[PDB]
Amino acid sequence: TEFWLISAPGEKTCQQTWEKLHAATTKNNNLAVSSKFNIPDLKVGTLDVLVGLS
Amino acid sequence: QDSYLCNVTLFKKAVDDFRHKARENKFIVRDFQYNEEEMRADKEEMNRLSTDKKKQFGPLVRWLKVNFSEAFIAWIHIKALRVFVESVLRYGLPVNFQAMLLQPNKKSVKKLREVLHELYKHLDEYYPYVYYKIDCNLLE
Amino acid sequence: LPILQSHSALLENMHIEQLARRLPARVQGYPWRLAYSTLEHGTSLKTLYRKSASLDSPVLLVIKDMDNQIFGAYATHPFRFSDHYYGTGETFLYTFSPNFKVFKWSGENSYFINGDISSLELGGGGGRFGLWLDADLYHGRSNSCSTFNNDILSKKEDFIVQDLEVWTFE
Amino acid sequence: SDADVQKQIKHMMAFIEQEANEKAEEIDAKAEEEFNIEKGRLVQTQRLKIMEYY
Image (cartoon, rainbow over all chains, first blue to last red; front, side, top):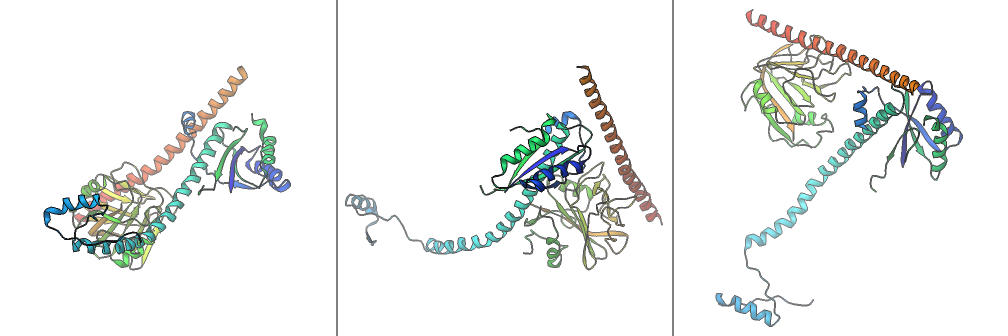
């Protein structure tokens, strides 16, 4: 058992990016099962915070 | 099978002389002196430990099965920070991204790696997208 | 299965059974140690803070009023002086009315615990408090507050403490 | 160079607007918290003095 989390921008909106990938990887070529992952609206710090967090 | 245990009785001085000359004669003094408190204690203790092991096992297994859950749940929340933070760094500051979970089929890895590269190479191990692996082989 | 306390003068096996089934996974299976008791350490809020000041673990507040009704709160962080609200959403209020009832966090706001120099209070949502206790641990009050959506924890909105315990899971 | 400076200025503008929105969010939250605290302390203090006088 293994999972890959990925994240990508909404090409204009979130739904498009998931559907487009799910079509390629899951509907058509059947290389992986896939679904959305539900990260909430977390509160961003300034840039000098995030470069520490990573 | 090899040997026997026997009494000797002697004048209280002679213990050192006897045990030395017994070792010279390859006769082995079994160094023990009687106390009924201790001869009771052996028979208490190997029953007691066999009992206390059974008292503790139940609560220990419930504590492990609960705190594995609490530490596993904590792990998935740290992935959910790492995908968030890196998607705020590697994409534009106005937050507009989707996180996705993929579960690869057997032997299919290269084709999937290639498809993801084809889907995202324009955003430019390293990848042109935010990525982290969640294992589940906890028992190694 | 009834959990391994070091004592209690307020609680009984009726109450310990019904509580040990509700506490969060964070304390399931720990022995309960008495941090403070008005019946052993003397009756003041400064003492309750002073006795709580060394902890780093959840606590159970237990109260008995002058009508002998038992109620209180389970609180994720020690009772301490604060200028702002603190604690997290596993905090809850409970009451033996004489049914055991528990009022877990509603999701509406994060006003769990607060503690001035002269009072201690739990809940919020307007001028409401789910529980409030004075500097003497003598007067106290309960109203329905929107953090927990509780019933009135005592028989009366305004109550007098007969005695109070704080347990901790260590 | 200078278009990429304008991209950096747009990122700075986005940070300025974002952290301004965060400051508005924080101050609006701390307004409602200190309303709950101050109202609650003030009523409960005076109500209890009245209760003992009568």
